[PDB]
Image (tube, rainbow, N blue to C red):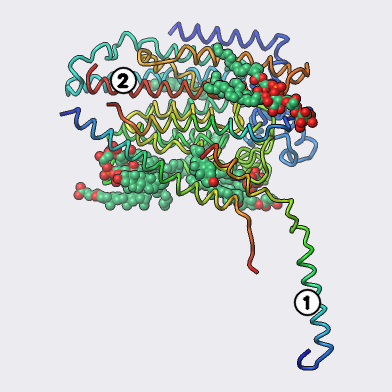
Amino acid sequence: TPDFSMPYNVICLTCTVVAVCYGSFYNLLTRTFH
Amino acid sequence: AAGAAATHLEVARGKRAALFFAAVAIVLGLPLWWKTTETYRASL
Amino acid sequence: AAPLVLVLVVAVTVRAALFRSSLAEFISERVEVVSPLSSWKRVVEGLSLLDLGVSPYSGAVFHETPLIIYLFHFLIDYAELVFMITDALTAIALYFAIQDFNKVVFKKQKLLLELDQYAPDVAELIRTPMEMRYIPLKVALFYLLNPYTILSCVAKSTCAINNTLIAFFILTTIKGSAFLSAIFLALATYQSLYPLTLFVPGLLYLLQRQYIPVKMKSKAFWIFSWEYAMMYVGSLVVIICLSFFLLSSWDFIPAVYGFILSVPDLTPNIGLFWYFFAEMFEHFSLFFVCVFQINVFFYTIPLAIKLKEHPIFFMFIQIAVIAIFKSYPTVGDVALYMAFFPVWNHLYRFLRNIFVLTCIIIVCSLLFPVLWHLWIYAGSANSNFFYAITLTFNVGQILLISDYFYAFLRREYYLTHGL
Amino acid sequence: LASGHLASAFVASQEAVTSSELAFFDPSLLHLLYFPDDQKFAIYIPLF
Ligand SMILES: CCCCCC/C=C\C=C/CCCCCCCC(=O)O[C@H](COC(=O)CCCCCCCCCCCCCCC)COP(=O)(O)O[C@@H]1[C@H](OC(=O)CCCCCCCCCCCCCCC)[C@H](O)[C@@H](O)[C@H](O)[C@H]1O[C@H]1O[C@H](CO)[C@@H](O[C@H]2O[C@H](CO)[C@@H](O)[C@H](O)[C@@H]2OP(=O)(O)OCCN)[C@H](O)[C@H]1N
Ligand SMILES: CC(C)CCC[C@@H](C)[C@H]1CC[C@H]2[C@@H]3CC=C4C[C@@H](OC(=O)CCC(=O)O)CC[C@]4(C)[C@H]3CC[C@]12C
Ligand SMILES: CC(C)CCC[C@@H](C)[C@H]1CC[C@H]2[C@@H]3CC=C4C[C@@H](OC(=O)CCC(=O)O)CC[C@]4(C)[C@H]3CC[C@]12C
Ligand SMILES: CC(C)CCC[C@@H](C)[C@H]1CC[C@H]2[C@@H]3CC=C4C[C@@H](OC(=O)CCC(=O)O)CC[C@]4(C)[C@H]3CC[C@]12C
Ligand SMILES: CC(C)CCC[C@@H](C)[C@H]1CC[C@H]2[C@@H]3CC=C4C[C@@H](OC(=O)CCC(=O)O)CC[C@]4(C)[C@H]3CC[C@]12C
Ligand SMILES: CC(C)CCC[C@@H](C)[C@H]1CC[C@H]2[C@@H]3CC=C4C[C@@H](O)CC[C@]4(C)[C@H]3CC[C@]12C
Ligand SMILES: CC(C)CCC[C@@H](C)[C@H]1CC[C@H]2[C@@H]3CC=C4C[C@@H](O)CC[C@]4(C)[C@H]3CC[C@]12C
Ligand SMILES: CC(C)CCC[C@@H](C)[C@H]1CC[C@H]2[C@@H]3CC=C4C[C@@H](O)CC[C@]4(C)[C@H]3CC[C@]12C
Ligand SMILES: CC(C)CCC[C@@H](C)[C@H]1CC[C@H]2[C@@H]3CC=C4C[C@@H](O)CC[C@]4(C)[C@H]3CC[C@]12C
Ligand SMILES: CC(C)CCC[C@@H](C)[C@H]1CC[C@H]2[C@@H]3CC=C4C[C@@H](O)CC[C@]4(C)[C@H]3CC[C@]12C
C-alpha cells in the first residue's frame, strides 16, 4: 500500500527536485564568466 | 584581438538561450495549463 | 593489445562465474535492475502465449517489440551467451571510437597552437600524447567492470542490447558514415523512444568533419541536413512497416510507445514517477504527465546553442539526462554515461564537491536493497523510506553532472583568456 | 394555447416538462465531483 496521509508533500518534493535541475541548467547556460 | 571576439560571441549566445527559455515558457505553459485544467461549460 | 584481451577475459570469467551460482535467481528479480520493459520472464511469457494461440499484446504483462520476439524465438536456448557477446561488442566499439576521437582532439588542438589564439601562459592545460595513451582501455574497463553492468547481464535484461545499439551509433558516427549512423539511430529509437534527441549532436559532428560551416545563409549545410533527416525517417518507416507483418497487427504500437508515454504501471523503481502518480489528485494528472515528459526533450535546443563546437560533450550530457528523467529507468542506463568519465578526467582540477557526491551515490546504491527488504518482507518499514532513497539518488546524479559541465566551461575560459 | 388548439398545446407542454426535468436531475450536476477552486494555488505554487 502507499501512504494515504501525504498526497500533498510528494508533489512539493518531486517538483523541488525538478526545479533544482532547471535552476542549475539555466544558470550554467545563460551566464558568462567575468 | 581574440579575447574581444570571444567575449562578444559568448554574450550573444547567452542572450539567445535566455530568449528561448522565456519564449517556450510562456508559449507552452500558459495554453497547456489553461486547456488541461479548465471547467468545460457549454452554452445556455 | 594484450591489455584489451586480458580485460575481456576477466569480464567474461566474472559473468560466467556469476551465472552458475545461487544468486542468479535473486539478482533476476530486483526492481532496480529490471523493468516492465526489460524483464526476461515477460519474454518467455509472450513466447508461451504465442504457442497457446493468444496474441502477446492482448494482456497486460508483455511490452516488447517484435524484433526481440524474432531474435529470442531463434535463440532461446543460447540466451546466456548472447548477453556476454553484446557486452563485449559495446566495450570494443567504445574503445575504437575513443581512439579516433583522441586523434581528432590532439590534431585540432595542435592546429590552434600555430594560429596562436591561446594565451601566453596557458600551459599545463595543454593535452599531451603521453596522457591520452590509456584513455580508451580505461573506458572499456569502466564499462565492463561496473557492478551495474554485471548485474544487468546476469539478469538477462534487454537494456544491454539498447546500450550496444547506442555504442554502435557513436562508433559509426565518429568513423564518418552517415547511412549507418542513421540506421543505428533508427534502431535505437524503435526500441526506446527517447534516443531521438541524439539526432542533433551527431549531425553537428558530421558537419564539422566535412568542414562545412554552420550558418543560416549556407547552402551545403541545408542539403546535408535534409539528406541526413530523410535517411533517418525512412529507416524508421521501413522498420515499422516490417514489424507489422510479423503478426499482421498494429497492436504492438500502443503496447510499447503508449506504455512508455502514459506510465500506467506503478511498480517501484529508482525513478521519479511511480510514487508521484500513486499519490496524485486526479484533476491534475494529465497536466503533470505532459510537463514531466516535456522535461526530457526540453534541454536539447539551448544545449545545442551553447555547445555548438563540442558535439561529443553534448552527447554525454544528453545521455545522462535521458538516463535520469526517463519513465522506467534502470541501472543499466546509468552505466552507459558513467563509462564516459575517463574521457573528461583532465578537468579534475576545476571540479568541486566531487568527493561528497561520490560517497552519497555509493551509499544510496547499498541502501536500496536493505530498505526494500524491510518494507516488503519484514513489514517494519513503509514506502516513504524507499521514496526518500530514490530522491537522494537522483539529486546526487544531477549535482554530479552539473559539476562536470561547470568544469568544462571554466577550462575553456582559462584557455582563451589566461590562467 | 393562445390560438385555441388544445391538443397540440398539450403535447408540447408534455415535451417541455420532460426535457426540463431531464436536464435538472442529471447525475453530473453534483457539486461533490469536482476539485475545489480554493485549493488550486497549493498545487500550482511548487513548480511555478
Ligand atoms: C542529501 C540531499 C537530500 C535531497 C532531498 C532529500 C530526500 C531524502 C532525504 C531525506 C528525507 C527527506 C524526504 C523524506 C520524506 C518522506 C520520508 C519520511 O520522512 O518518512 C520516514 C522515512 O524515514 C527516513 O526518511 C530516513 C530513513 C532512511 C533514509 C535515509 C535518508 C537518506 C540517506 C541517504 C544518504 C545518508 C548518508 C549519505 C552521506 C554519506 C518514515 O517515518 P514515518 O512514516 O513514521 O513518518 C511519516 C511522515 O514523516 C515525514 O515524512 C516527515 C515530513 C517532512 C519530511 C521532509 C523533510 C523536509 C526537508 C528534508 C531535508 C533534506 C535535505 C535537503 C536539502 C539538500 C509524516 O510526518 C506523516 O504525514 C506520515 O504519514 C508519517 O507516517 C505515519 O504517520 C501517521 C501517523 O502514524 C499515519 O497516518 C495514518 O494513521 C492516522 C491515524 O492517527 C490517520 O489519521 C491517517 O489517515 C493515516 O491513515 P490510516 O487510517 O492509519 O491507514 C493505515 C493503513 N496503512 C501513517 O500511516 C504513518 N505511516
Ligand atoms: C525557418 C523554417 C522555415 C525552417 C526551414 C528552413 C528554411 C528557412 C531554409 C531552407 C533552405 C534555406 C535557403 C537555402 C539557400 C539559400 C541561399 C543563400 O544564398 C546563397 O546561396 C547565395 C550564394 C552566393 O552568392 O554565394 C541565402 C539563404 C537561402 C535562401 C536559405 C534561406 C533559409 C532556407 C529557406
Ligand atoms: C515513420 C514515422 C515517422 C510515422 C509513420 C509510421 C506509420 C507507417 C505508422 C506509425 C503509427 C501508425 C498508426 C498507429 C495506430 C493506429 C491505430 C489503428 O487503429 C486500430 O484499428 C487499433 C485497434 C483496433 O484494431 O481496433 C489503425 C492504424 C493506426 C492509425 C496506425 C497507422 C500506421 C502508422 C501511422
Ligand atoms: C522520430 C519521429 C519523426 C517520430 C517518432 C515516432 C513517434 C512520433 C510515434 C511512433 C509511435 C507513436 C505512438 C503509437 C501509438 C500510440 C497510442 C495512442 O493511443 C493510446 O493508446 C494512447 C495511450 C493512452 O492514452 O492510454 C496514442 C498515441 C501513441 C502513444 C503514439 C504516439 C506517437 C508515437 C510514439
Ligand atoms: C519531439 C517530440 C517527442 C515532441 C516533444 C515532446 C512533447 C512536447 C510531447 C511528445 C510526446 C508527448 C506525450 C505523448 C503521450 C502522452 C500520454 C498522455 O496520456 C493520456 O492522455 C492518458 C491519460 C493520462 O494519463 O492523463 C499524456 C500526455 C503524454 C505523456 C504526452 C506529453 C507531451 C509529449 C511528451
Ligand atoms: C525548434 C525551435 C527552433 C523552434 C521553437 C521556438 C523557439 C526555439 C524560437 C521561438 C522564438 C525564437 C526567438 C525569437 C527571436 C530571437 C532574437 C534573435 O536575436 C536571436 C534568436 C531569438 C532569441 C529566437 C530564438 C529561438 C526562439 C526562442
Ligand atoms: C519542466 C520543463 C522541462 C518542461 C515544461 C516547462 C514549462 C512549459 C512548464 C513547467 C511548469 C509549468 C508551470 C507550473 C504551474 C503553473 C501555475 C499555473 O497556475 C499557471 C501555469 C504555471 C505557471 C505553469 C506554466 C508552464 C510551466 C512553467
Ligand atoms: C559482425 C558483427 C556481429 C559485430 C562487429 C564487430 C567488429 C567486427 C567491429 C565492431 C567495431 C569495429 C571497428 C570500429 C572502428 C575501426 C577503426 C577503423 O579505422 C578500422 C576498423 C575498426 C578497427 C573496426 C574493425 C571492426 C570492428 C571491431
Ligand atoms: C530490420 C533491421 C535489422 C533494420 C535493417 C536495416 C534497415 C534500417 C534498412 C533496410 C532498408 C533501408 C532503407 C533503404 C532505402 C532508403 C532510401 C534512402 O533515400 C534513405 C534511407 C532508406 C530509407 C533506408 C533506411 C534504412 C533501411 C530501412
Ligand atoms: C511538436 C512537438 C515537438 C512539441 C509540441 C508538444 C506536444 C508533443 C504536446 C504538448 C502538449 C500536449 C497535449 C497536452 C494535453 C492533451 C490533452 C489530451 O487530449 C491528451 C493529449 C494532449 C492533446 C497532448 C498531446 C501532445 C501535446 C500537444
* Vertical comparison of C91 with C67: above or below: above
- The kind of secondary structure element at disc 1 is helix
Labels 2 and 1 positioned on one and the same chain: no
Residue B35 located left or right of residue C224: right
| Residue C105 location (% of width, % of height) | 31, 21
Q: Amino acid at mark 1?
A: Ala
* Vertical comparison of C131 with B19: above or below: above
Tell me what residue is drawn at x 37 percent, y 32 percent.
A29
Residue C46 located left or right of residue C182: right
Q: Which residue is mark 1?
A: D16
Say which of C276 and C3 sits in front. Answer: C276
- The chain ID associated with circle 1 is D
The quarter of the picture where residue B43 lies is bottom right
Quarter occupied by the C terminus of chain C: top left
The quarter of the picture where residue C343 lies is top left
* Vertical comparison of C417 with B40: above or below: above
The quarter of the picture where residue B13 lies is top left
| Residue A24 location (% of width, % of height) | 44, 29
- The chain ID associated with circle 2 is C
| Residue C32 location (% of width, % of height) | 64, 22
Q: Amino acid at mark 2?
A: Arg
Tell me what residue is drawn at x 23 percent, y 34 percent.
B8
Residue A14 located left or right of residue C251: left
Q: Which residue is mark 2?
A: C411
